[PDB]
Length: 268
Image (cartoon, rainbow, N blue to C red):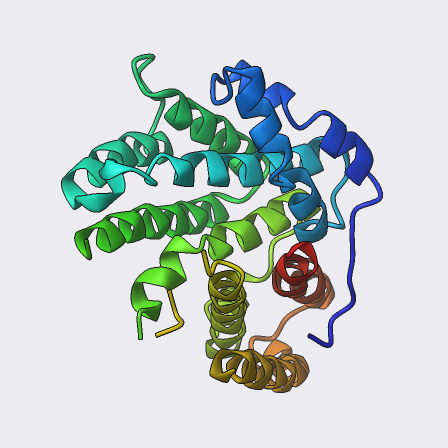
């Protein structure tokens, strides 16, 4: 991974305060669960996904990593074995994208809603709508994988890389030009980011894509990622980006796409 390792300078404070949010939302209710949460290294992971964020912006990234693993743990048992029960929970979480949740919603849903509320604020409506679709793809992917009980079609959505990348924009208080986000070149870059994350995850998860060749695919995809990066100057002219748009595209390349590729590696 020819990308620099980066970590937010506010990582220590973010890690020290990481428990206050999931406790106030009822996601962590016992001292033992708090310690199990601390052992995951989730604030550390967030500080590497979002080295450009500090303070509340980084706290939102910490909470997303916190929520990710608290959420995924709810499907480790029987619920993850049938799609109907998986969907019953995911629909309650995903409903937060469409409006306020009933007070009766499970705590994991109110926690997501508090993340999503903070994610959207200050971003363009079109960015919000696109990020909301990425979430729905993520929740729909959990139902697809439960219905299963080249696996990339399901895993590319359940790995949660795109909402991670989305949050890097919000945490950096910038948006990549929407027409460049939809570009075939950026789409290929994001697909590499997703594929590298799920490959590195299945390797560290031997306790699955294993069914040597995976390490070469990570290397081939990262070499292609560099080629795709070299096309970005011409992509910017094709879409007639102005100066601020070229800078936002550059921030997206370095603080969102590169970070999500490198950060998971350094965290593992």
